[PDB]
Length: 166
Ligand SMILES: Nc1nc2c(ncn2[C@@H]2O[C@H](COP(=O)(O)OP(=O)(O)NP(=O)(O)O)[C@@H](O)[C@H]2O)c(=O)[nH]1
Ligand SMILES: [Ca+2]
Ligand SMILES: [Mg+2]
Ligand SMILES: [Mg+2]
Image 1 (tube, helix red, strand yellow):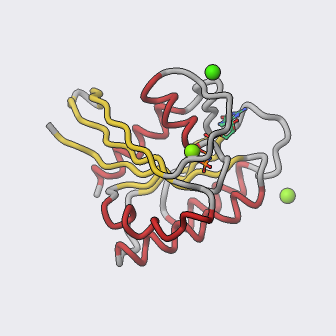
Image 2 (tube, rainbow, N blue to C red):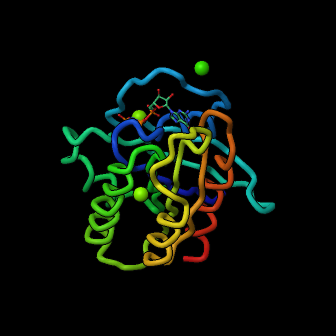
């Protein structure tokens, strides 16, 4: 069966682990344990096709930035996550995308931009601001809440589907 190698990236605390754990294990992680680098795998049917999701949950803490090249070499598609209540995390998205593009030596890398924590009302990144950034990349923008599950499957499955247009 087809295996898809997904990598979840973004600034510390934007909800990468919570997003991944909600997809794979169907519960919300309320506590904040910073990640170094974890792996998850799951068999899912997407558009009538059985496939294996291999998901790498990466470190947002800048301390582990040296590990980025290795996983950007391996990953097939990148979920680029910021939190809609954390403008700096939105501003940090580009540093992840620029490096993925260098490492891949390509402008056409399967990616989805994700504005997470859309359940929270303290919004400082407006959806239109993120839409404009996604448009410049030529990639989808999808808002999510790892807490309520809104958009969680859509974001990951859209990323699968971008690796398939590729
Ligand atoms: N309300 C709300 N809280 C969320 C959401 N996603 C994550 N959080 C909360 O935000 C905190 C950080 O979550 P986490 O998933 O660990 O972020 P991270 O991006 O994995 N951090 P790191 O880069 O250090 O591994 C946790 O307390 C988590 O419960 C969301 O969609 N909504
Ligand atoms: Ca919980
Ligand atoms: Mg984490
Ligand atoms: Mg503003």
